[PDB]
Image: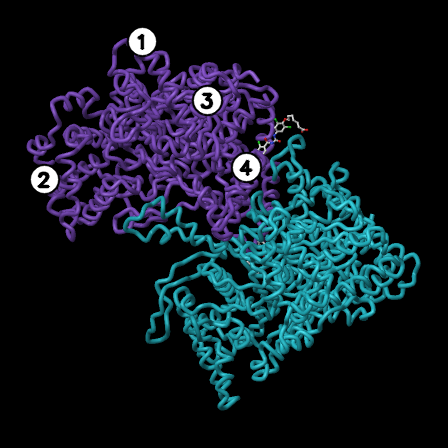
Chain colours: A cyan, B purple
């Protein structure tokens, strides 16, 4: 079998008895009545057993050596399943495969039983998960801090072509990976008021909610390092949430506890969109308040807080955990009694902020009346921070009164708001973008004034993905043939993939690379009929666009191309065209009307196209249901063409693009986010770039975007729009897509029409190349061999050195 | 050490490594950071490991042999801690004691860490728990069915002498004894409406709530039998509780799931009192609906339901699970399509009902509009049952029109109600009382008309307690000296205690019995200062009354005696009186104003009495906080005098009385409930009986109870009442106890004054005997040696033979 580890005689035997120990003592079942779910748990407990020994010594190790600790705060950690990933990082995969085989079970069948830990929306949360893996693999004393939602991202269902949302009760049957830690439970305060006494302000009459931590192990890749991801759960105190007496009802008081505990109940399903709800703000303060107490308690052990920044680094994944800044000041000033200036120096030195987007609707601007009621003391601290900061600005730019209001953390107008992004820049010693072009846009546009004030704060850290889950785990076949030629060191040193460049003309390698992709497509095509049912052709080109549904991602632009292909076939039926299976998948936030309308359009197109006899098997339009991490692990390795077509300047970085490049797909996209660095790495000749560059978009905005012009000059485009308008795709409801057509024609913020012509022209070129298997595969080799820069191990090493001030190490911890 | 088992060489070694296995792999801790709570869990998992092997074979056994199954339905199971009880029934106590000792830990200290499973209010719920233990010990294929409340009976706190209630979050840190079983999850329906079609009625448009079962092991005493207690948890479906579309909010829909799940959130804290709230009715149907589906599924395996009653017996613990009758009919008739009459014959033959009280306010009378809305089909079935039953009555008593309305299940008046007790009698083949006198009262009074209609249904089954938890567990010292003389067979054959009668004159035994009681009192006196702090004298007579606070239990009568003792001391300070420490403990339902006023009176008396220098150590009044099962295990073995002073005819049976008799306390009480059979068993000369008999109470009611008469003729009583009235016990609030005085004088339903004189006269006699250690101990021996009849093994054997139709067996199951 492959390089999924050794299947040692002693270890396969040991594994089997432990599997049986758990099936008996843990699941209290006997072979006779054991369900595949029982078997999955017996294995999970058996595999988990192998890392507790290492988990304990890693933590004990950091206590003894006492290195600088890295705290990654995020309201999202899109982890996915954890059984296989643990086997991989522990080199247990083959031994486990063999052992379950001897026990007469199919390991792959059991793996499918594990529920995804979908505590994330998309890119932002998956990054945090890839980062955790890399920090462990690079031997960093890092902790992931977040919220333990009992309901993660909703499960998407398609009814009559429409998306239906349903609760993701991922804890229903239990989580074998987490470990509750009821000794470090902590109190978090809300509401109350501020009393200004003689020796300081006091936050008084607050409502208390407890934060209970749950630890999940994060194993490094084959180095015996197991870090921790600590997730907080909300718990109501038993006293006041019952003890605030004088009528109301005892029963009611108890039932009302589910009011303080609602804080960790569900994840907000918004991707790149801000919703100013109180529950969201509560979650944000909750994770911040509890995490900081835990961070300081650990430090107090390790009171001059001058050394605090030398032992602590806290990274802010977006502005979601931005209250960490005024909260750190509160504790230092109100509780520890440090002077403002010393406190601020410490705060700025330990905090760092990462920006993930530039769209305005994604920006966090919290109404002042909300902060005023829920966190009175924090609002005071924010005003004081703002006051001193603006004084700095005035001193630097004398008389520049407009600059002052532009830079304020407080925004005036309808209702006063607090710009959380301005708060983060002011209280952090480093601010970074997630891709070179996004980082430049931050300096030139959005945060230009701040860059002029303190240029040294702004940096770039291009995103990356973990080659463990995103290669070895999901594509063992590709990982194996690569290993046959260059060894296994590349798994933790992706740059070595470049060595594959010298096999670009190797006849055996070209055949192998092409064979694994074929086996991957056949397996996906099978899975499709198995779990979703209705056939596809594995010989066609697999055209896939999978990511959250957004107007800026332009799934709509993809739709226009699909309809074009269809119309051309209907025009010249007996003309040869390269067969394609275009798959589009992704979730739409529940309140995002337009995004939900786009899902219906995709399914509507499929209804027409998939049942037209003249089309035959030359074109199928499929909507991939419930796109999530586990589903991504299946489609990506099977894709031929990766769609990354966002309007230039809107996708900060993207990471799915990197996943496809590493797995043998060719990319068709715009010069946006990381797409630029990828084409720069592979060579533009090995990439399918099209459309407007950032500057063309700006030129168009100066002159003014008029979709009618495009509609007027392109007959094919006009024909499509008139098809949608007349009900060609919605017979029973002819005006069903009027909102889409209306928007495309009059309020398209992302100029879909502007890139239409260059997009279908470019798609013609990919079809031309696909007709030449050998050359397509050779270009594929050029992409894979050149994807090494996009490993999160490179990203993390850069954060470590340029922001945290710590040195990565690939040293194996002293055995388990 | 005692007879807590053998401390085998191989087993103490095995125990230790398993303790360490769990501390490492299960608790993921290392000796260095392990908290006593971690140690408690390591041990709990180690002990639990020893019964899973037996649990599996016991269940497998019942499947193979297929005996008649006994289903005990109760909304209450007052279990208490389970670590020690499991050790005892498995004969692991010494081995575990030795092993933890070698590991350098104190087993007793770890035991105190376990949280009580307080899923009961008092007598009714503790009975169910004693019964479960006995059914396992007698080798019966029995299952306990109930609700898994996440919050059991509230924890009682005394603030300023007042009771404060606080949420009992007993699952906070986890339950090592239960095992979730997510494969047998079941749907339960609510609301909806009834469609009458062509071939039957249909319950339609219902709201669905899921019932998830959790199994807890119930080990028999040293026979390798481990039965199951299955507790249901409410879970919201992920669909409709989200899928019923058309605006409302996605977040809100998810947060609203805690509406269907509130059904199993908290136990109603009412003891012998009915509260017609909808949530209560929902809990009642919930446990019934889920249990029945599970019972029928098991039977379908084992479709002629003629054999149903031959394989199934379901016992109703009070009327709480009474909906099992119309629910069984619904399934049989609506779903299985059996004719009414065949269905009714089956239902009556499998159901049996146990009555626990005769007070009217405890009787369940559900408003028809409530049943009409929540369970429309069940109301129809109840009307049909009533119709046919009354027809039976009319046929038997022609022209007796008043008898007809008296017997109806439907009560007319203000609002129509359904008398659940009448429902149970009609649909059950057996109805029993819980003590001989209570059973006679049922036939003569409350259910007289029903008895005349079907005399064969009415039986008696005097309650009992388990000698395992209520002797061996809580009083090993007494269990040991008994064993030294008559052996160990009495633990599962309590009648053998009679053999102790021949040692009544044994000088060594008298000294031993007296010594263990002294050691018990010293340990309790210590525990008092340890956890509650404020000294007591262990040489005094321990006068204790512990049970729920109720007007019928007459804690108030106890209070009058205490005040009398105090007043007499103040009158003749230098006169000798037998020292006493009177302890009163118990919880009051949160809405029970009078009961809460009584707790304040007790603490108020203590405030005066405990600080009067003239009194010295001759009299202390102590209120035992948070009385529960674990606290009962401590006080009872230390008590000298047991107070069972309810008004004759009000306490159905009582069980605390039996606990005290078995543990060396003498009893002062009225001829009520089981007190009558206890004095009859021990000989009235060895009991301190006083007050009115049932007949005297009735004579008084005919003539009319006038408390003033007593107040007028007894100066001591008058003096007490004037002390309460003038604020002698409440200086700052002189009229604080006006409600108590007002009630005592004008609306005393339980004639406290009527038994006052005979009560203090009798108390004088117990003090006289206490002055003679040797004779007190000899009388104590007469009680213990004669308590064997009160074992739940005797009660269960009777239920088995006279109601269920099964034969008990003390046969050891074929090893683990
Ligand atoms: O194995 C097959 O291939 C199916 C054989 C079906 C024929 C009857 C088998 O007899 C059995 C056997 Cl072998 C085992 C069991 N039961 C538990 O293992 N386990 C439990 O019941 C159990 C499960 C969880 C928690 C507590 C318990 Cl006690 C119950 C019965 Cl009835
Ligand atoms: O034992 C004493 O007497 C106290 C000794 C204090 C001095 C430092 C000891 O060094 C240690 C040692 Cl020995 C052990 C640990 N940690 C775990 O065992 N266990 C965990 O951290 C742990 C606990 C639950 C779930 C997951 C983990 Cl990783 C952590 C550290 Cl820092």
Note whether residue A35 is visible. yes
* Contact check, label 4 and label 3, Cβ < 8 Å: no
Does the beta carbon at disc 2 come under 8 Å from ligand 2?
A: no
Number of the front mark, 4 or 3: 3
Query: Which residue in the structure is indicated by mark 3?
Result: B329
Mark 2 or mark 4: which comes first in sequence? Answer: 4
The quadrant where residue B444 appears: top left
Q: CA distance from mark 2 to mark 1?
A: 58 Å
**Is label 1 in contact with label 4 (beta carbons under 8 Å)?**
no
Which label's residue is closer to the chain start, 2 or 1? 1
- The kind of secondary structure element at disc 1 is helix
Residue nearest the viewer, comparing A641 with B256? A641
Whether callout 2 and callout 1 share a subunit is answered: yes
Spot occupied by residue B79 in the image (x, y as percentages of width and height)? 43, 35
| Residue with the most extreme left position | B712
Q: Quadrant of ligand 2?
A: bottom right
Q: In the rendered view of the protein, which quadrant contains the C terminus of chain B?
A: top right
- First reached walking from the N terminus: tag 3 or tag 1: 3
- Report the residue marked by disc 4: B95
- The Cα–Cα distance between marks 2 and 3, rounded to whole angstroms, is 61 Å
Label 3: which secondary element: helix
Image disc number at residue B396: 1
Q: Please identify, in this view, whether the residue under mark 2 or under mark 4 is nearer the observer.
A: 2
Q: Position of residue B365 (x, y in %)?
A: 32, 29
Say which of marks 1 and 4 sits in front: 1
**Residue denoted by label 2:** B719
Q: CA distance from mark 4 to mark 3?
A: 51 Å
Left or right: B579 as drawn, with respect to A453: left
Q: Chain of mark 4?
A: B
Which one is closest to the eye, mark 2 or mark 1? 1
């Amino acid at each position: 079998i492959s390089v999924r580890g050794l299947a040692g005689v002693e270890n396969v035997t040991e594994l089997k008895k432990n599997f049986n120990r758990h099936l008996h003592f843990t699941l209290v079942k006997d072979r006779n009545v054991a369900t595949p779910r029982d078997y999955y748990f017996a294995l999970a407990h058996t595999v988990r057993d192998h890392l507790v020994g290492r988990w304990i010594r890693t933590q004990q190790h950091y206590y003894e050596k006492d290195p600088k600790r890295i705290y990654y705060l995020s309201l999202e950690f899109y982890m996915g399943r954890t059984l296989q990933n643990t086997m991989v990082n522990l080199a247990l995969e083959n031994a486990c495969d063999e052992a379950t085989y001897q026990l007469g079970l199919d390991m792959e069948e059991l793996e499918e039983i594990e529920e995804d830990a979908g505590l994330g929306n998309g890119g932002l949360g998956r990054l945090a998960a890839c980062f955790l893996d890399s920090m462990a693999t690079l031997g960093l004393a890092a902790y992931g801090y977040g919220i333990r939602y009992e309901f993660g991202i909703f499960n998407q269902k398609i009814c009559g072509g429409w998306q239906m949302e349903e609760a993701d009760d991922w804890l229903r049957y239990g989580n074998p990976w987490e470990k509750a830690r009821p000794e470090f439970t902590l109190p978090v305060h809300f509401y109350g008021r501020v009393e200004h006494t003689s020796q300081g302000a006091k936050w008084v009459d607050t409502q208390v909610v407890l934060a209970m931590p749950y630890d999940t192990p994060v194993p490094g890749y084959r180095n015996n390092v197991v870090n921790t991801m600590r997730l907080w759960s909300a718990k109501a105190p038993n006293d006041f949430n019952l003890k605030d007496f004088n009528v109301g009802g005892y029963i009611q008081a108890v039932l009302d506890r589910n009011l303080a505990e609602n804080i960790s109940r569900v994840l907000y399903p918004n991707d790149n969109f801000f919703e100013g709800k109180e529950l969201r703000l509560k979650q944000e303060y909750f994770v911040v308040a509890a995490t900081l107490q835990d961070i300081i308690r650990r430090f107090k052990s390790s009171t001059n807080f001058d050394a605090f920044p030398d032992k602590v680094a806290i990274q802010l994944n977006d502005t979601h955990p931005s209250l960490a800044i005024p909260e750190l000041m509160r504790v230092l000033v109100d509780l520890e009694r440090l002077d403002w200036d010393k406190a601020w120096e410490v705060t700025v030195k330990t905090c760092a902020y990462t920006n993930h987007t530039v769209i305005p609707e994604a920006l966090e601007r919290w109404p002042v009346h909300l902060l005023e009621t829920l966190l009175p003391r924090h609002l005071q601290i924010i005003y004081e921070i703002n006051q001193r900061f603006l004084n700095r600005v005035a001193a630097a730019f004398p008389g520049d009164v407009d600059r002052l209001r532009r830079m304020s953390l407080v925004e005036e107008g309808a209702v006063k708001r607090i710009n959380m992004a301005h708060l983060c820049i002011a209280g952090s010693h480093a601010v970074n973008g997630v891709a070179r072009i996004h980082s430049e846009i931050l300096k030139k546009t959005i945060f230009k004034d701040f860059y002029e004030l303190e240029p040294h704060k702004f940096q770039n850290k291009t995103n990356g993905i973990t080659p463990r889950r995103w290669l070895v785990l999901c594509n063992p076949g590709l990982a194996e043939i690569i290993a046959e030629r260059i060894g296994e060191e590349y798994i933790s040193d992706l740059d070595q993939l470049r060595k594959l460049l010298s096999y670009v003309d190797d006849e055996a390698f070209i055949r192998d690379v092409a064979k694994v992709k074929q086996e991957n497509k056949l397996k996906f095509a099978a899975y499709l009929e198995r779990e979703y049912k209705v056939h596809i052709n594995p010989n066609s080109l697999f055209d896939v666009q999978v990511k959250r549904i957004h107007e800026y991602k332009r799934q709509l632009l993809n739709c226009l191309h699909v309809i074009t292909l269809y119309n051309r076939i209907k025009k010249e039926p007996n003309k040869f065209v390269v067969p394609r299976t275009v798959m589009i998948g992704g979730k739409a936030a529940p309140g995002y009307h337009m995004a939900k309308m786009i899902i219906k359009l995709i399914t509507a197109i499929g209804d027409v196209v998939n049942h037209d006899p003249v089309v035959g098997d030359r074109l199928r339009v499929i909507f991939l249901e419930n796109y999530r991490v586990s589903l991504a692990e299946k489609v990506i390795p099977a894709a031929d063409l990766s769609e990354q077509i966002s309007t230039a300047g809107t996708e900060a970085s993207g990471t799915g693009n990197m996943k496809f490049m590493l797995n043998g797909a060719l990319t068709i996209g715009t010069m946006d986010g990381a797409n630029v660095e990828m084409a720069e790495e592979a060579g533009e000749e090995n990439f399918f770039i099209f459309g407007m560059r950032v500057e063309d978009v700006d030129r168009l905005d100066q002159r003014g975007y008029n979709a009618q012009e495009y509609y007027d000059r392109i007959p094919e485009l006009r024909q499509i729009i008139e098809q949608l308008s007349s009900g060609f795709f919605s017979p029973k409801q002819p005006d069903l897509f009027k909102d889409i057509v209306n928007m495309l024609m009059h309020h398209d913020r992302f100029k879909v029409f502007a890139d239409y012509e260059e997009y279908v022209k470019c798609q013609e070129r990919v079809s031309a190349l696909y007709k030449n298997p050998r050359e397509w595969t050779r270009m594929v080799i050029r992409n894979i061999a050149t994807s090494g820069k996009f490993s999160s191990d490179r990203t993390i090493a850069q954060y470590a050195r340029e922001i945290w001030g710590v040195e990565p190490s690939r040293q194996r911890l002293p055995a388990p």
